[PDB]
RNA sequence: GUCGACGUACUUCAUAGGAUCA
RNA sequence: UAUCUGGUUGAUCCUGCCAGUAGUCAUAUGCUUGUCUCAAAGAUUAAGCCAUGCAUGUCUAAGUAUAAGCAAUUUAUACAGUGAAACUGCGAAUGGCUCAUUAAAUCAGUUAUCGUUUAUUUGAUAGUUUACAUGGUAUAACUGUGGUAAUUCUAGAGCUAAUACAUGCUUAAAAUCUCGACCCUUUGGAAGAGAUGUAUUUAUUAGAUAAAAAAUCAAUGUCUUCGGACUCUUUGAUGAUUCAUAAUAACUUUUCGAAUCGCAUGGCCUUGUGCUGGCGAUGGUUCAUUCAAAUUUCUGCCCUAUCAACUUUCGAUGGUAGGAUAGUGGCCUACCAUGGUUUCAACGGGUAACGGGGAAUAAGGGUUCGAUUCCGGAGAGGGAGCCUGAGAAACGGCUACCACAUCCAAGGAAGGCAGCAGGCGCGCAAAUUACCCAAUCCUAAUUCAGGGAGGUAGUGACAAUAAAUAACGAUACAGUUGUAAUUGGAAUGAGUACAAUGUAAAUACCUUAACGAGGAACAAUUGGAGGGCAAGUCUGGUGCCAGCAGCCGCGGUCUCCAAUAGCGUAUAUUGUUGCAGUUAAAAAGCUCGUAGUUGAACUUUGGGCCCGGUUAACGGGGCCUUUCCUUCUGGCUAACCUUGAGCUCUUGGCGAACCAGGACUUUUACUUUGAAAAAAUUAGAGUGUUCAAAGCAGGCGUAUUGCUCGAAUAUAUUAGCAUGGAAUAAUAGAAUAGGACGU
């Protein structure tokens, strides 16, 4: 190619969007934004294919141009705005607030939240560095640059960002016994407690996570997101509480509830 | 014409590679800018991205730094005396990085006169007495000062930045280059 | 595929030139203007010599037999 | 272009079409169940082969193997639901013992014959293709329709059918009009 | 030239035996 | 091969042999071709040539309208509604097509940028720079005068705008650092004058630390109890940096720091068109993020040894310095050395070689195919070279040359279908030069415009699913069976068609008034096998016969078998597991010998206890047994001693184990487990698409408002990463001791 691509075939689109393979030939390409392409849910798919509010792309554009959709407390109008992990989607007319969280199956789940819990978000500190004029700043997983951080905040910590002011309200250190959420890999969507961090200089760090059912799994450190202390999450978790269930047990539960 | 691709070269084993593709713009090269002493002539070059480069086709002044005294003064370049890569640049008086040049000493000499009150208001006297301890300098630099032309080394790249900055040779640097001269 | 017979070599003469050069470099072991200008006999000779050298039909079967029998 | 739509063959030619015993068995099956051609028998043989191969593969695995348990339970459930496998025979061993005739039995043509709506299997086929038979509240015009245990009790003449309480067909009212005239 | 060698491709000849019976 | 059929003679058996009978896939071709769903369209190794048409343009309240544009209007004598043309900004580098070149190249997996650019999005970020606001250093559109046969050709003159072009001010305090008039000779002081944001270039400085105490020389600062005293004194990140950042001195054809636009008219008053003030758009330096780009580490490619040496003069390997690059780098230049690969197959040659996900077959190993729905690479007739722009070596951008080829008034001009349709390449052939942006998403100043991308329908049975062509009776005839141009009234869709549904508009599907069946002539096919007939014809002979065969005679103008809406014809279709080498393929005349492959045994075995797991067996851990890695530091602190209050608290010691880090360190092979290996595909769970192929849908209540489950799971070779094992196969150590340890 001679430049950046602007099209996305349906088959090449991220699996977890759950797009029909025969509805069309192309899929929404998320525009550049806070989140990466493969780890983002564009607003069109959220409003049309998940909430079923809009029947087709044109109605989604009609919704957005009315300025009813807010992402992280700011109005967005791009149909392909890449909403992602820990972003708050507010629809005032419906009096609805959503937080985008992966369910156990690894897909973004429609999770309804109260307004108070919608007042803030959580961000993984991706970088801590001194800016120009000797001003420290922190860059989070969603690309927010926050100046004058608390000095104790280090990389891989979690910061609770208030959306109204864009400032850090509190922070959680990455330590053993903390509650964490998996945001990548085959263990995507699971929740557990840290047990031990293996360090490999010049390589990818590994973290052992024990679930509430005492099952253990190892995951690369880049895919871990600290969300609180054990039993005291700082956000409301989706149904299932991040517990992975075997196929047989899922069958049993499904038959029972039916 | 000029290209920086590694494909046209032979492999490590000595095999003659075939032409994988046509030449690409992102691996281009441009003609050298044989900078020379004379009235200032600099023309811009639009490079990759929106960035810009400056081509020093002609130049006669440069900022030179005396490191020992930690000063930098602007001075005309007398000429090129010795270059390590190729002598033809010395014969043609072409300015490039690391070329050894001769520059006038008048600004540096005047600065040393003013700062130390020696030669190569009570406020001035007090300051001079305070700084008198550091007055002594190398004999080699002083001899050039007497001659009026100091030996300097260009640390900038005129073909890229459009500047001719440098620093005064000193110590082992000066001894070695004097031996080579 | 390097030197395979083409449908119309005469249409792609320049291509053949490259091939010849490659051969000259690859088989060497065995043997031993600016168009972007404001204003744009030896070159006629260059045209003739290059086009003739690139395009010479291989000496035919019956032609080999004829030379042998004439000898 | 648009993503592919999957397709598959539902039948395969037998290893030996020319065996006399096979020809006789095909004749017997076709006559008993009123099948149009050998393609139906080949289709049902293909399905039964697929199920029995799967049953073999699951049996090969160790007992209590989670894949074995899950897949065997699903297969036995499906076979029991469709009516081929009886309630008391819920073991993969008895799945492996199934025969083609059991599948031919569940066909809507055979069931329509057995329940007494038709005097012949061919009459049942004609009734089905003429939109006279309804499973539940729904008209089905496909003899190869496989009837489930729940659905077997709801086979009846369709409401729109002249035999199901609707108006007489074209022939009947045509003759009645001619007689009236 | 109904030429030699080789390569290639084909054709062809070699299948009945033991037991009983007349 | 297999089963079955037939031949092997004077016959019948038992062997053996021979001939024919298997297969889907692939190409070409023939005959037929009613309905529903669904879906594809390459091929002369010709990436050969193309007429005609279309396929990229774009405007919101928010850059520029005195169009002599339209329409309203005194809701405007600066404009304001809408708005052609043009300037300006953005896009045109996406998409679509093809597989020519390409054999460590591409590509797959896995790494790196502490080696670099990045329009845009997102978040931060700039009191340090006539102003009630500067120019033509200027023009388009437009008016008007013209040239040429001709083209998206344009010449002179006259005008006029900017978020175009080019300039240029306006805003707190403080601190610090220089130069310093002057009083004065002090321990000096000091009015004043300067400089500081960013951007570039260079030189220099800071960016500390395994842990504790003193004596002086020089400079020299706070303090007191005038003696001496002087404490809490500042520094982030990485495994690692000259990193982030800061500071000092200068430098620059040198930048940036809002002379822009919409909507609205709030608050203070000293009542001034005074001061102050909201919600947005668009610009702008730097940093980060995102979409990306470039290079890059390890492993992996078919045939060829009758290709054994290759690369190096004209860069091949490496060092140094420079040029260039966005940047590393022989990428190039100058000087240097003589290097680099190779029987573990380099180099050269062939490739009907784009690579992969995948497809076919097979019981397993394997073998073949993969132009072709997705990813990545390259190309736009063939070479070469460039403007623009963040992004191009672009070709529906430009320039030359090579080859073709169009117009021509002969002076000149214009070309690139391997985009969608549609032609030529033969004298023998095959989709429509159709409709639409309604769904998918993409582009723009942007909800609206545009989109042969894409969708819709049409068109050779590509490949696939379902499935009509009759069902129930009576009578008759013939040797309880078979046959009906016999006969009765019931059913129904192929088709026709009101209507409605469907669709952007249509067609079709599903529905459905009304028509639509006895030769149900509403007339099913493709192959094979076997008969019988004459005042007939040919041929041969131990009479009247036999073979061939028989649409033809004197006149006159038939039965059965197979598949089935599908059927036929032609070509094509090696042993690792695991082959053989005396007598019927193949052991070299013998020996030596390099590479390669292979290579005797031995090193902690056994025994005694403890714990908790499975279904008395089996596995999993701890100890003990001469068996514990070593060392330092840090963190917590058990147990162990003890006082006191009732095995639990508590006082003061001692602090094992465990955890964190620095030092200390034989290396692999093998094997276990965990991540990773896109989606699609394969297997596979659920789901009455009317069944099925499929799809990821759906399901349950319902007077009213609604509730709700899903879109699972498994597989993937080699390489790289992490981890448990210590059996098997290697590898290093103490021999002139240059060996181990130390309070
Ligand atoms: Mg790293
Ligand atoms: Mg009906
Ligand atoms: Mg035909
Ligand atoms: Mg018909
Ligand atoms: Mg119909
Ligand atoms: Mg080759
Ligand atoms: Mg490689
Ligand atoms: Mg843009
Ligand atoms: Mg921005
Ligand atoms: Mg003019
Ligand atoms: Mg050289
Ligand atoms: Mg270098
Ligand atoms: Mg090829
Ligand atoms: Mg291939
Ligand atoms: Mg391919
Ligand atoms: Mg290209
Ligand atoms: Mg062509
Ligand atoms: Mg080109
Ligand atoms: Mg193009
Ligand atoms: Mg074209
Ligand atoms: Mg075409
Ligand atoms: Mg098409
Ligand atoms: Mg605008
Ligand atoms: Mg039709
Ligand atoms: Mg040897
Ligand atoms: Mg051994
Ligand atoms: Mg592996």
Image: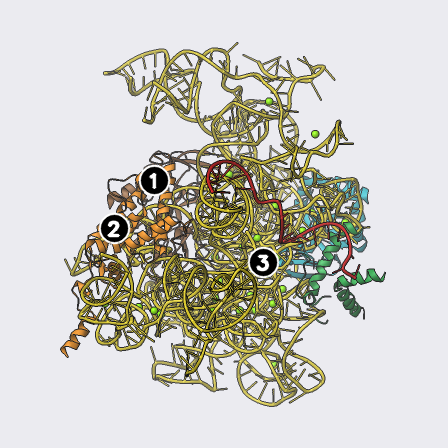
Chain colours: A brown, B cyan, C green, D orange, E red, F yellow
**Above or below F239: residue D154:** below
Label 1 vs label 3, nearer the camera: 1
Look at mark 1 in the image and give the residue it sits on: A246
Pinpoint residue D45: horizontal percent, then vertical percent.
Answer: 36, 49
Pinpoint residue F426: horizontal percent, then vertical percent.
Answer: 61, 73
Pinpoint residue F341: horizontal percent, then vertical percent.
Answer: 70, 41
**The residue marked by circle 2 belongs to what chain?**
D
Q: Residue at x 69, y 62 (%)?
A: C15
**Above or below D125: residue A155:** above
Look at mark 2 in the image and give the residue it sits on: D148
Q: Specify whether tag 1 is near ligand 27 (CB below 8 Å).
A: no
Counting the numbered discs, the total is 3
Element assignment for label 3: loop
Find residue F61 and report its image quarter: bottom left
Q: Which mark is residue B49?
A: 3
Q: Specify whether tag 2 is near ligand 2 (CB below 8 Å).
A: no
- Closer to the camera in the image, F242 or F614: F614
CA separation, marks 1 and 3? 53 Å
- Residue B87 in sight here: yes
- Closer to the camera in the image, A196 or B60: A196
Check the image and name the residue furthest to the right. C71
- Mark 1: few, some, or many residues within 10 Å (few <14, many ≥20)? few
Q: Is residue F289 left or right of residue B33?
A: left
């Amino acid at each position: 190619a001679r430049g950046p691509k602007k099209h996305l075939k349906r088959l090449a689109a991220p699996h977890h969007w759950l797009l029909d393979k025969l509805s069309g030939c192309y899929a929404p390409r998320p525009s550049a934004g806070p989140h990466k392409l493969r780890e983002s849910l564009p607003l069109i798919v959220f409003l049309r294919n998940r909430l079923k509010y809009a029947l087709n792309g044109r109605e989604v554009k009609a919704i957005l141009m009315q300025r009813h959709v807010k992402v992280d407390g700011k109005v967005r109008t791009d149909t392909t705005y890449p909403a992602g992990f820990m972003d708050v989607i507010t629809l005032d007319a419906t009096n609805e607030n959503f937080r985008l969280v992966y369910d156990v199956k690894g897909r973004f789940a429609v999770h309804r939240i109260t307004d108070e819990e919608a007042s803030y978000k959580l961000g993984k500190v991706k970088k801590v560095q001194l800016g120009k004029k000797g001003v420290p700043y922190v860059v989070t997983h969603d690309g927010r640059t926050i100046r004058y951080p608390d000095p104790n905040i280090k990389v891989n910590d979690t910061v609770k960002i208030d959306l109204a002011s864009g400032k850090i309200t509190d922070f959680i250190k990455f330590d053993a016994g903390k509650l964490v959420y998996v945001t990548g890999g085959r263990n995507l969507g699971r929740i557990g407690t840290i047990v031990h961090k293996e360090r490999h200089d010049g390589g990818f760090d590994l973290v052992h996570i024990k679930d509430s059912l005492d099952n253990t799994f190892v995951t690369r450190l880049n895919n871990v997101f600290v969300i609180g202390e054990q039993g005291k999450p700082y956000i409301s978790l989706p149904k299932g509480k991040g517990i992975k269930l075997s196929i047989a047990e899922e069958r049993d539960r499904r038959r029972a509830q039916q | 014409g000029i290209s920086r691709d590694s494909r046209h070269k032979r492999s490590a084993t000595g095999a003659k590679r075939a032409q994988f593709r046509k030449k690409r713009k992102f691996e281009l090269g441009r003609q050298p800018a044989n900078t020379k002493i004379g009235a200032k002539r600099i023309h811009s070059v639009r490079t990759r991205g929106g960035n810009k480069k400056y081509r020093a086709l002609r130049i006669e002044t440069g900022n030179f730094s005396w490191a020992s005294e930690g000063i930098s003064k602007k001075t005309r370049i007398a000429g090129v005396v010795y270059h390590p890569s190729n002598n033809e640049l010395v014969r043609t008086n072409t300015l490039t990085k690391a070329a050894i040049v001769q520059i006038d000493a008048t600004p540096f000499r005047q600065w040393f006169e003013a700062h130390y009150g020696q030669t190569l208001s009570k406020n001035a006297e007090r300051k001079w007495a305070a700084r008198a301890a550091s007055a002594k300098i190398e004999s080699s630099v002083e001899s050039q000062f007497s001659a009026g032309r100091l030996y300097a080394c260009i640390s900038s790249r005129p073909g890229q930045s459009g500047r001719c900055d440098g620093y005064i040779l000193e110590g082992e640097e000066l001894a070695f280059y004097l031996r080579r001269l | 595929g390097t030197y395979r017979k083409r449908f119309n070599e005469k249409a792609r003469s320049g291509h053949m030139a490259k091939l010849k050069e490659l051969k000259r470099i690859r088989n060497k072991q065995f043997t031993r203007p600016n168009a972007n200008a404001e204003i744009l006999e030896e070159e006629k000779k260059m045209k003739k010599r290059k086009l003739q050298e690139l395009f010479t039909p291989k000496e035919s079967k019956v032609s080999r037999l004829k030379k042998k029998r004439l000898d | 272009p648009r993503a592919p739509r999957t397709y598959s063959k539902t039948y395969s030619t037998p290893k030996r079409p020319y065996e006399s015993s096979r020809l006789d068995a095909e004749l017997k099956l076709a006559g008993e169940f009123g099948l149009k051609n050998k393609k139906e028998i080949y289709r049902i043989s293909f399905q039964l082969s697929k199920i029995r191969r799967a049953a073999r593969d699951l049996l090969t695995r160790d007992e209590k193997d989670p894949k074995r348990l899950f897949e065997g339970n699903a297969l036995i459930r499906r076979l029991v639901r469709v009516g081929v496998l009886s309630e008391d025979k819920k073991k993969l061993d008895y799945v492996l013992a199934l025969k083609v005739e059991d599948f031919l039995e569940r066909r809507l043509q055979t069931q329509v014959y057995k329940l007494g709506l038709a005097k012949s299997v061919h009459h049942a086929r004609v009734l089905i293709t003429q939109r006279h038979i309804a499973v539940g509240k729904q008209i089905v015009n496909i003899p190869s329709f496989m009837v489930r245990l729940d659905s077997e009790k709801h086979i009846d003449f369709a409401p729109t059918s002249p035999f199901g309480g609707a108006r007489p067909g074209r022939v009947a009212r045509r003759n009645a009009a001619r007689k009236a005239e």
